[PDB]
Image 1: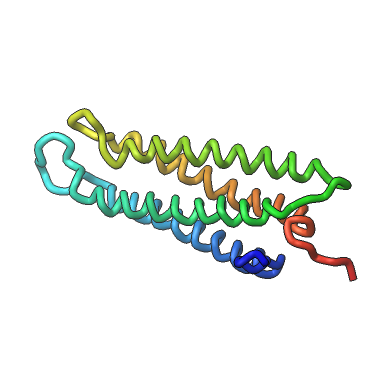
Image 2: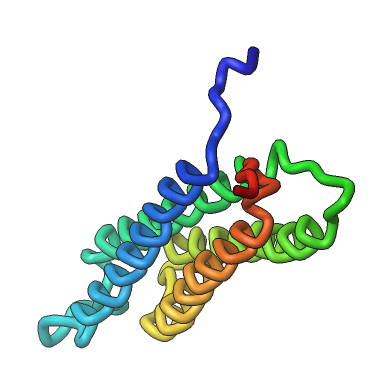
Length: 163
């Protein structure tokens, strides 16, 4: 049965390949938007001169994170249905890097959710963005490396027979 149809390595490789482009493409936007933050714009603008273009920043950070979650889901779908008593280090190596991504991905959401709003008057300063742009580069770099671990065990995540 299984209402959902099985996934093949080619589909997993094809669908996952889109995530690497959408992730590398989305992260590029974060740096492209930072260029616009070259200056506060205008001469004087009360405290926290920056604030109006926050929606543009909130949209890019949420968009880049959205593609990563798809990687967590895509990697998760491949990790599932994965069984093989003969092998086990791959799951340990993949689970170690995948679970680390899970813990690291939720840590940025809280740090990122803070940039969205703050109980105090001011939310964050441009300085925090230098750290956010820094963490944003860490998540996608790991997405590419995790893709390599999926390949070393892709044969088990899906099947792939030997010719």
